[PDB]
Image (tube, coloured by chain):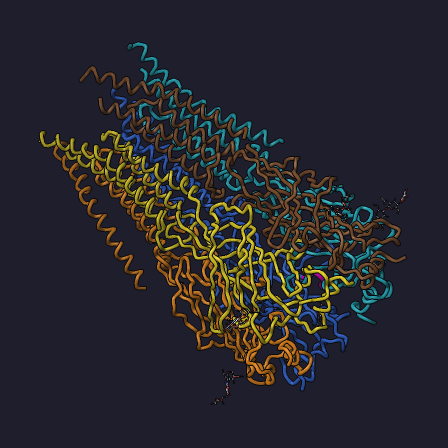
Chain colours: A cyan, B brown, C blue, D yellow, E orange
Amino acid sequence: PMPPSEFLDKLMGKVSGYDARIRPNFKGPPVNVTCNIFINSFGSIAETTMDYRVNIFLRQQWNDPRLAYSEYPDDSLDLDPSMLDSIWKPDLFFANEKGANFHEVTTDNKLLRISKNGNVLYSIRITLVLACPMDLKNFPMDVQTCIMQLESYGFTMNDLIFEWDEKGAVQVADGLTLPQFILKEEKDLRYCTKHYNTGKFTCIEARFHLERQMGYYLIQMYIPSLLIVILSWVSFWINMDAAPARVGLGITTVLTMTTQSSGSRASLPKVSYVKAIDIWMAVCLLFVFSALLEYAAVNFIARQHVEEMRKLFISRAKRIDTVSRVAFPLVFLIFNIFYWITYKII
Amino acid sequence: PMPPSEFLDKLMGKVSGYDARIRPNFKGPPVNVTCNIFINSFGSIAETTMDYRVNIFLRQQWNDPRLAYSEYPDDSLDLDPSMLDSIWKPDLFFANEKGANFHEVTTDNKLLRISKNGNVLYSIRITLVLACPMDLKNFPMDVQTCIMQLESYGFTMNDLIFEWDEKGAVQVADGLTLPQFILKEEKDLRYCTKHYNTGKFTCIEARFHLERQMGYYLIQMYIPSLLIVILSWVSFWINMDAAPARVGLGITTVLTMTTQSSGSRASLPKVSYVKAIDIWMAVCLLFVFSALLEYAAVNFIARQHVEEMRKLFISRAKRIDTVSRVAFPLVFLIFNIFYWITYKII
Amino acid sequence: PMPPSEFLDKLMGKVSGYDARIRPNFKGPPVNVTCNIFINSFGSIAETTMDYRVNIFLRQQWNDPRLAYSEYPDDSLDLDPSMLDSIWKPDLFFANEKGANFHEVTTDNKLLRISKNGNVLYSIRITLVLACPMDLKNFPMDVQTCIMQLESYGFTMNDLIFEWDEKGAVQVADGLTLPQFILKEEKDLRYCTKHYNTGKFTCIEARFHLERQMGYYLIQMYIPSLLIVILSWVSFWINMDAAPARVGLGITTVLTMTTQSSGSRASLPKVSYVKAIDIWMAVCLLFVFSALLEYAAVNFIARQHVEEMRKLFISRAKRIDTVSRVAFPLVFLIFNIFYWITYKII
Amino acid sequence: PMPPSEFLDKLMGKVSGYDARIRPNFKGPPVNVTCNIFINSFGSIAETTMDYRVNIFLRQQWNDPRLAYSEYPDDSLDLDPSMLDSIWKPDLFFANEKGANFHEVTTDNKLLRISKNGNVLYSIRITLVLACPMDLKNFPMDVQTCIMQLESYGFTMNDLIFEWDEKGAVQVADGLTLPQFILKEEKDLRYCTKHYNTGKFTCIEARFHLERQMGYYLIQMYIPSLLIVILSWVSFWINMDAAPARVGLGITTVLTMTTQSSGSRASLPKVSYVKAIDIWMAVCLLFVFSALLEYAAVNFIARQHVEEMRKLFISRAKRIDTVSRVAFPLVFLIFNIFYWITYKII
Amino acid sequence: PMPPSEFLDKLMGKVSGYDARIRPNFKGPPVNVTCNIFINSFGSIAETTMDYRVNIFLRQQWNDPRLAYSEYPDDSLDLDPSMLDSIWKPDLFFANEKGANFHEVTTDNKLLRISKNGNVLYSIRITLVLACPMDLKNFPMDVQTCIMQLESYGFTMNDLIFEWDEKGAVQVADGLTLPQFILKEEKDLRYCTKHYNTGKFTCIEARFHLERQMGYYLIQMYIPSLLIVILSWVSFWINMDAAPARVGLGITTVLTMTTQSSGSRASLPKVSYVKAIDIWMAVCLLFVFSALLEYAAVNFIARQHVEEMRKLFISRAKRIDTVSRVAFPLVFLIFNIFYWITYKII
Ligand SMILES: *[C@@H]1O[C@H](CO)[C@@H](O[C@@H]2O[C@H](CO)[C@@H](O[C@@H]3O[C@H](CO)[C@@H](O)[C@H](O)[C@@H]3O)[C@H](O)[C@H]2NC(C)=O)[C@H](O)[C@H]1NC(C)=O
Ligand SMILES: *[C@@H]1O[C@H](CO)[C@@H](O[C@@H]2O[C@H](CO)[C@@H](O[C@@H]3O[C@H](CO)[C@@H](O)[C@H](O)[C@@H]3O)[C@H](O)[C@H]2NC(C)=O)[C@H](O)[C@H]1NC(C)=O
Ligand SMILES: *[C@@H]1O[C@H](CO)[C@@H](O[C@@H]2O[C@H](CO)[C@@H](O[C@@H]3O[C@H](CO)[C@@H](O)[C@H](O)[C@@H]3O)[C@H](O)[C@H]2NC(C)=O)[C@H](O)[C@H]1NC(C)=O
Ligand SMILES: *[C@@H]1O[C@H](CO)[C@@H](O[C@@H]2O[C@H](CO)[C@@H](O[C@@H]3O[C@H](CO)[C@@H](O)[C@H](O)[C@@H]3O)[C@H](O)[C@H]2NC(C)=O)[C@H](O)[C@H]1NC(C)=O
Ligand SMILES: *[C@@H]1O[C@H](CO)[C@@H](O[C@@H]2O[C@H](CO)[C@@H](O[C@@H]3O[C@H](CO)[C@@H](O)[C@H](O)[C@@H]3O)[C@H](O)[C@H]2NC(C)=O)[C@H](O)[C@H]1NC(C)=O
């Protein structure tokens, strides 16, 4: 017999009237193309530009009666990736590409096989940098949901319809790990049918829940953010007579805590709303600032102190020192409870 | 009958004398091309290079009598995006491109349909990085106006005219949100007809008002910029005898405020004029510097103090301490009123 | 006779039925392609994106009976790199490309020679940026293993099989040096046969062990990380009466050590687990923090001190000063032993 | 009649012997090509790499007798930008390109019109990143001169000559503003004829004077650079008995001034010569360092002070304090005059 | 007669049997191609990636008897750069490209002329980013030697040999200046013949000595690195009774010197060996650390001081103060001599 390359020349050549500019089943029902992606590499999720780089295998399957051969004895004929400009292909595109490219390492990474009944498998490797609106109302304890939509651009709903297959619409790699987030096993599948001034177009999308890993932020901006508050608590255990001791403590600590506040949003987007890490530094900033005002109240009584009425001012300046050793270690603990409970339920 | 691919070969082939290098209605009136864009993604507005990345759908509509078919029973014939090099297309370009590229993810993102009367719709996806002169006279409270002009390069006014359509000249996406700014619903539409040494060319543009969100700057460079001034106010409530207490306070605070001034223009363009954030740090720098000179005036009187005339110098050195507790908390409030009123009207 | 260019036109032209879209030995055994790479340049191994740039010479050898000439008197015929689109080539690709490109400096860097029996050598220069999961459980003393897999995309196992040659499967350059790591002479060779929903494909890979050089981290983040702890030890040799001396020492040192902790993960990925450099700064942070609490215990006894019972409190406040000069210099040495032994065996 | 597309096929087709590989007026005088650029966008002038990005409209005009039509009734025939590979074009190139690209947004931005006498206008949009040797002998008050040369590569002087036109050789945009520098209205026009081992080639260039705007540097690195010196002057108004007051002032200020010196060359090229900003920080570093040595001379006399001869040492230690309040405020003013006069004339 | 474009069609057309896939002098001696480069732009030598960007004019000259015309009366025929795909060209490539590109600004920057005897000149503009192993054993006083090799990829030694010409093998631009380094006039020329598993290939290279300019490092990291040591010397001229004076001096200076050590390797590669700038900061770190231990020895004697034996401890605590004023100013000078002598000979 003849090889599949010469066998398909009768179906993709000048004979049989086959044209790559004509969609299958013309003047009839639209083409129902089913798609399924395979995430190979994931990560590099930046927040300054609010985008993430993904590498998926976009599989496409449809039905073309013009390529339904019945003379070849086999059931699957592989095609050279250099002959993709001869058959019709869906005009699939993403609405959040923001720059993309293919891979042509020694061969155009394309897969093309034709079944006997007319099933055509089209799998290619695409490297996308997808964008998603980052919701940072609770930055250290948020559940991001970055989606990706597959719309049409040249054909409307009556000519091309995208759908998901029931046999693993979205597969995940075996050893796919992320440096900062984690990929949940549950991925939603809903439609995203858009409507413009020209018409209506099909759209398919899949939700991806990306939960953060609190192990990183808990060590860098939570343990040092708590030890600095302890530095302001040791001033109560120091005598009220040493002026340079408690003054230098209430100033060097209250100024190095601002660096922690400025160092908590160094690589974060400039959002207007307040996040969960801005209420942890601001409240702890009040503790390192109230300790400065605490010494300002103790030193103000000692500098004012008549022999009987002045002996009570010394005890009054020391009575507040007996409560500050218990108030702040018990008030900061109350805020430490309302913080790790409210942001663990919402 | 015959498919539209073979039907349009009579209108785009060697027959009928149709050439892609000839504009419609030659030796007559110019081609009136109407355009309308659809902003899909917006943001990433940097200030060091004074540019912003945009992703729009550039729709183009004109009239070509050479493509006015009258035999096909339908009213809209979709075209393959691979056949855009056969018909005439307007030479539309932007005067502020500064690098651009198309999107060819599995298909050239182009839309092409031809009506019966000769209406040709041309919609493509372009990713532009547009530039605009940043007016930073009031940096935290400015209303930026970044525009984009669509000029001609090969045809003059007598051969190609660009205009805006009245049915939604500029559409906005449904869920288009910006991280730093906000997009106003009012967009101006005016002409930008340029004149060069070669001739005159058409030009269409649309204004985009981008108001900032003060919620970000109010927390990072306004709350810490005010608490440092309070650190210089607590020196008045400290006795005038402790030298290392008030000296270290008037130096560590006046030097950490300069870091806030240098940290306020870390990612800003090097403009010559003064902005609204440079007058907030410089005036607050005077308060943290006047407190240093305030102790220099109190300590200078105590070191100079004859038994009757010296008792008044001690009261004089304490009389200024009774006014500094009221002057600065009431003078900084006056500047706090004139600042948030002048920059809220202009 | 005729030159090899005209001699091979009979084997690569329209005659002999040779087609570049047909794999050798069709309807029979699969093509056994042996590959061997030659690493020219290596390094630039970043950790923020977890990727490294490599430049190898990908050699490919297979058997094509359709190109087995028997009339030319020579044994090796060199081919012009501009004629690679006429013969069949394996669709080799990498599963961790993440962007790649060729080199076309004055000539496409391709090698093509055909033997008499049908051996075809295919060598090209590819610049890859390969990714690997960075295991940073012990950051300064880890042995990274970055691999690279060569999979198929268009042909399954029954049509294309990749294998390694026994004569130097992976060669190393003569003067290939790395700035940070070192390349070990032992490189493992194992298979990576994947299985997808479409079928099974061949895969070959080679392990690369990249041991770090501790000479860099030992000087920058280990010598200064130890001298700061010595600054907290000198407070014991200072009299317990000078308050501003020991207070300023226990605060300026405990706050500059946090900068060393924040400066140890400035260009590191945001991992959740704790690494070996996070337990060296945190434990040393306890020493510079216990010295602050040590003075808080000595000053608390002196401020409390009845004529006979008060003379023992002065000796008690000095007895701890006689143990702190020996405890911390001997407790930090114990942690210094358990650290450099546990992380030198695992 | 026939359209210009079919009319010019007789002049650009196989007939008439017109070839795009032959320069006009062969075996005779060279082609005198006149050029004129139009700067659209300017700025982004970095100093680390010593380059600036420019966007100009390169117009080219020459004479081609082979295209001198005499049958068409019009005087200017516009050409499709897709037919630039049919006529001869000058091989113009820049000697300081360092990477460049064109703009192909929906159309190749090319202009091509042919006059009756043979005048051919060629205007294209080129985005260049031009380099210039940065002369930073006086960094805040220099007048940079970045030029751009247009050389030939394939034709020598006897075959191609570039010249400037007298009617606006270099035009400037109407609203072209720069963020840091300013563009002067005077632009020099001189030749740059080079000589290599192959021969001599034509060259045209234009000088661009880029004066800096001192409004930026005067606020960031000149006002804080002067207030720190004032902090060292207030130590003279403090009593000579307070040791921790004047010691901490002469150390915290002398160390934060070094940050201003290191912060003045953070984004500057590593040049060997000294600039005008390195002599302003180094001299001011002497003032904040002489104040430290001033207290070292006052405290050395007080610690040495026999009942009559010791009373003069106290007055001697205070006599220098009466001159330091007048010397430094009058010596720093002398350097402040010689600085803003020498660098305002050269 | 006929123009050179039509004259060379007889030598580059279907007639005469000329093929671009055949090297000259086949079945005979190899082609001796002589090359000579012309460095136009040089600099941008980074150290994090260990690469430098260069822009050279790669001239190539060989002998092709098939192009030896004898009928044209001239001696040099210029060729259009669009016809380089018709003649044979050497497959020259660099072994350290790491990404490269050509320049196509309005014309492919290629030079092609053919002599009567068969001499063919081939000059193109290539922008390379070449790599070299940075030897940083003495960072401020090293002599870097970055080379560039021109190897073959498709032809072995018996088919293509590269050589250097004796008439200026490597030329330098007239006004080529470097921001950091300097280019020496002496450039070595040696061979780099490599040997692989396939065979042996020709190779030509040229050495480039790049000496650093010490004027930059001497001001930024050598003058401030010496003044901080002077701050530790002034503590000896202060009385031994002021505790907060000498304690704060021996801590604030010893901690700001570590920033100079961390600030000396901010943009340097992470090498394991010690460089010449790491022994200048570490030794100076001992001086600012020995001054802290010097006060720890003086204060330890004063706190210990029986009426006759205690008067000698006061003199002993002051005797070391009389030697420290002379020891350190004379020991640091000894290290200052051995440093600037050992690194000025090797
Ligand atoms: C692609 O998928 C669409 C569905 O999304 C298919 O369209 C549906 O096709 C049926 C005929 O097969 C149309 O008729 C209906 O038939 C059912 C019985 O199956 C009957 O109960 C209904 O009353 C109706 O007559 C139906 O209108 C149509 N639906 C839509 C929304 O178009 C289409 O056939 C598929 N195309 C191919 C090539 O498989
Ligand atoms: C494209 O749009 C232009 C307008 O911007 C159209 O041009 C105008 O066309 C009219 C004829 O239709 C020209 O004549 C005028 O007619 C009015 C009555 O409608 C009459 O009152 C005037 O006195 C005049 O005779 C008019 O001069 C012309 N204007 C310009 C500025 O060119 C043009 O026809 C449109 N082209 C197409 C193909 O639709
Ligand atoms: C490519 O390599 C494969 C092996 O990976 C070759 O396949 C093996 O080929 C033999 C025949 O040569 C097949 O038959 C076996 O022969 C042995 C004797 O050599 C006999 O003991 C066995 O019982 C069996 O009959 C064998 O099944 C086959 N193995 C596989 C896994 O396919 C193949 O021939 C190679 N192709 C070329 C073109 O060299
Ligand atoms: C392109 O420009 C060059 C000048 O840069 C033109 O060349 C000059 O052409 C004249 C003839 O037109 C040559 O002859 C001279 O004529 C003058 C009178 O005009 C006479 O006084 C002189 O003694 C001499 O005979 C002249 O040598 C030549 N100069 C050079 C440097 O080539 C050239 O003609 C222009 N080409 C075109 C096509 O316009
Ligand atoms: C390209 O350069 C090579 C040299 O690198 C040329 O090869 C040498 O060519 C000579 C003949 O011209 C060969 O023969 C020798 O001749 C000398 C007298 O000149 C004689 O004393 C020797 O005993 C020997 O017979 C020589 O073997 C050969 N050397 C090599 C290494 O190949 C070659 O001819 C040049 N090609 C062209 C086209 O110019």
Is D148 rendered above or below residue D178?
below
Q: Is residue A306 left or right of residue B345?
A: left
Q: Residue D290: x, y in percent?
A: 26, 41
Q: Which residue occupies the foreground of this view, D80 or B146?
A: D80
Q: Which residue occupies the foreground of this view, A66 or D192?
A: D192
Q: Is residue A227 visible?
A: no
Q: Is residue C157 magenta?
A: yes
Q: Which residue occupies the foreground of this view, E85 or C106?
A: E85
Task: Choose top left, top right, bottom left or bottom right for residue E8.
Answer: bottom right
Q: Is residue C172 left or right of residue E258?
A: right
Q: Residue D25: x, y in percent?
A: 60, 72
Q: Residue D332: x, y in percent?
A: 28, 40
Where does the magenta region start and end? C152-158
Q: Is residue E185 magenta?
A: no
Task: Choose top left, top right, bottom left or bottom right for residue D3.
Answer: bottom right
Q: Is residue B16 visible?
A: yes
Count of labels in the image: 0
Q: Is residue B321 left or right of residue E270?
A: left
For the point 34% across and 14% down, the residue is: A313
Q: Residue C271: x, y in percent?
A: 54, 45
Quadrant (top left, top right, bottom left, bottom right) of the N terminus of chain C: bottom right
Q: Which residue occupies the foreground of this view, C52 or A48?
A: A48
Task: Choose top left, top right, bottom left or bottom right for residue C75.
Answer: bottom right
For the point 47% across and 73% down, the residue is: D197
Q: Is residue D7 left or right of residue B178?
A: right
Is B85 rendered above or below residue C140?
below
Main SS class of the magenta portion in the image: loop
